[PDB]
Image 1 (cartoon, rainbow, N blue to C red):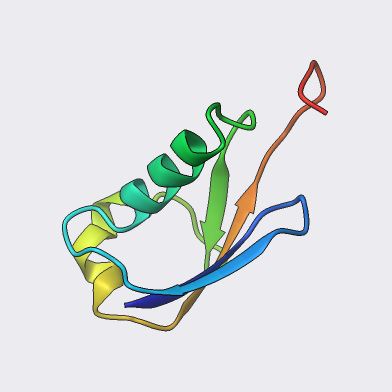
Image 2 (cartoon, rainbow, N blue to C red):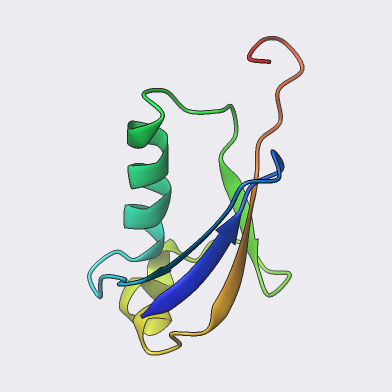
Length: 78
């Protein structure tokens, strides 16, 4: 339900309304679309683990899982 996503840009956003179909994919996809374009890698780590798309609905039952997004930009995108 409620999740806190913080990017490497020191941007933390805490919302209390997550989906049960995608959740993760929806969150990451909505963040990239909101900014217009993807930062670079757009890879977040959940509980020190990766790949959470498969836990779309499984993440909706948490409603208390800290999320940290990472964007690797060395070529361009300051």
